[PDB]
Structures are given as structure tokens and as C-alpha cells.
Image (spheres, grey):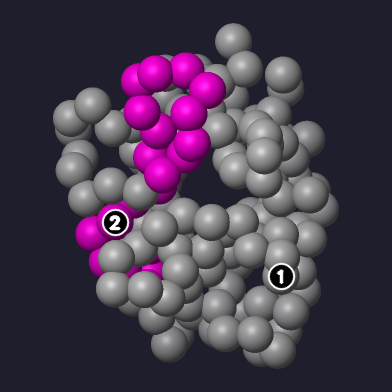
Amino acid sequence: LCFRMKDSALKVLYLHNNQLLAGGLIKGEEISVVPNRWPEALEQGRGSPVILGVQGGSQCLSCGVGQEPTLTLEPVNIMELYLGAKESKSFTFYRADAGLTSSFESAAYPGWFLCTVPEADQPVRLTQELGKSYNTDFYFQQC
């Protein structure tokens, strides 16, 4: 079971040039949202830890391992992340549910949230700034 996502401005998340973009105003990329198998080792008051995949979970979103986070799709199967074969923390987001929408906070880089910008058809990225121009709230639709 997968989800399609939109930001709260109704921009559809889809893939182009191996990047998640927000636009398509396109039904959206089918995104795998998989709970981390070992949540006790993480900060769960921030939301439920999940790994986000695309293309049937054959690539997963990472914040990287640099000093400054940056969002990339990495060619790792969610199965390997979910198994313990690969370490998962840079690929883990805390999903906070507000009811209509969810936000996604980097487990590896606290205070950074998945977000979109106002301009159409731009990359999904990360931000520390809430309530400003960056949109950190997302709708799910089930596939």
C-alpha cells in the first residue's frame, strides 16, 4: 500500500530528473511510508519515525551525512533500511500528524522539516523555518 502526497497548497509530489518536485497543476509519485522497525532507539515524541521511498521503495529519501542536510533520493531499497542491512537514521523522518496533514522532521538533523516552496515544479527540500514561505504540511491520499 502506497500514498500519494500533496503539500497543503495542493501541489502534487512527483519525480523528475531523479528528484521529488512539487507541482503537477499528474496524480503523483506513489510514495512508500514505512515505520522504522526500531523506534525505541529514536526520539518518538517528535512523531512516528518513518522511511520514505519512491518507485516501489527502490529509492529512499535521505538527508545525507554532511554537516548541512540536503535532500537526495538514494538508490537503496527500503527493505535493506528496514532490515538493519543499512543504517537508517539519515533516511528517518518523524511524522507528526495534525489530523488533516502531516509534517516530516529529519531524525538525523533535528529541527529540519521536509518542505516545498511557493513556485511551481521545484524540488522538495528541507527547512528550519516554520510558518513562513516554506510549506511543511502534507496531505496523503491512499493508492
Quarter holding the C terminus is top right
Left-right relation of 90 to 56: left
Residue 27, by quadrant, is top right
Kindly identify which numbered label has been placed on residue 112: 2
Classify mark 2: helix, strand or loop.
loop
Q: Main secondary structure of the magenta part?
A: loop
Picture mark count: 2
Amino acid carrying label 1: it is Val
Horizontal arrangement in the rendering, residue 52 relative to residue 143 (left or right): left
User: Residue 107, position in %: x, y?
Assistant: 38, 70
Q: Nearer the viewer, mark 1 or mark 2?
A: 1
Q: Residue at x 43, y 87 (%)?
A: 41
Q: What type is the residue that disc 2 sits on?
A: Trp
Q: Is residue 110 magenta?
A: yes
Mark on residue 76?
Answer: 1
Q: Which residues are magenta?
A: 106-125
Instruction: Please state the horizontal and vertical placement of residue 57, each as a whole percent of the image.
Output: 76, 58
- Asked if the residue at tag 2 contacts the one at tag 1, i.e. Cβ–Cβ closer than 8 Å, the answer is no
| 30 vs 96: above or below | above
Alpha-carbon span between mark 1 and mark 2? 22 Å
Give the structural element (helix, strand or loop) at label 1.
Answer: loop
Vertical arrangement, residue 78 with respect to residue 6, above or below? below
* 42 left or right of 79 in image: left
- Position of 117 with respect to 13 (left or right) is left
Does residue 128 appear anywhere in the picture?
Answer: yes
Q: Earlier in the sequence, mark 1 or mark 2?
A: 1
Q: Residue at x 35, y 49 (%)?
A: 126
